[PDB]
Length: 233
Length: 54
Ligand SMILES: C[N+](C)(C)CCCN1C(=O)[C@@H]2[C@H](C1=O)[C@H](c1coc(-c3ccc(Cl)s3)n1)N1CCC[C@@H]21
Ligand code: NA
Ligand code: NA
Image: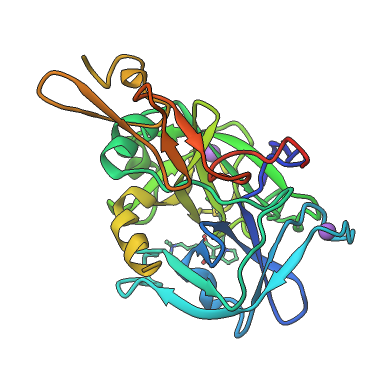
């Protein structure tokens, strides 16, 4: 996350961290239930093997509430394409269930039509993660969040050097130096409605981070709400 | 009555019928007797920040 702020205790409890063959974070995810994590399909190619950490806010401190879970099943979207990042979505089933607690709780899955009319029409959503704090920088050791404006699709397409499919949306700022970044990849974009946070996006890609005239690109979760339900059984 | 004005007074999901609105809630909540509010069924309902240390 470039700009934004550190997540306060209890404020980002749906954040998951995928950890590679080093206990190093390389992507985010979103807690959906005791057994399921939502992430980006493109993250699955970035480490041969990985585990999921929940409850972490500071990767350099053993607070005591963190827990690591192994992955039992990876359910990648069967139309995911590395060339365009179209269909950039996956669900992970964990081998053991998450115990919800301080800093560990699921984000809500909204009903589709209402999400389209009511969530995607809000001014902003929130993105979070442990990703880089500037494009050429290093990952944050502390969990950050950022309020990102929804950006209309026509503006989105004109801004981009690459195709923006209807499975994607833009969020963020034209010139203000705030954005998601590498390492936030796969993590949550949620939208608040009367103090309840609903899953609306997955951090997918960008042309650099916080560049002038570029936006962050997110997987459009409304397009996949039925797919998520099926994937979770 | 309409979902476009104050979300039909629903706490969460709103859908319009011929004359009325119908409210509903995400899993882990029960729609209240008033037909509008969503009541959590457990201590870590989806979408809520964990601010009351139990
Ligand atoms: C056109 N398309 C193929 C989708 C571009 C993919 C570009 N891209 C990569 O190749 C990945 C990923 C990314 O977005 C990642 C990256 C850079 O910036 C970001 C983000 C910026 C804003 C976001 Cl929202 S995600 N992700 N790159 C740095 C490390 C891996 C590589
Ligand atoms: Na920690
Ligand atoms: Na920008």
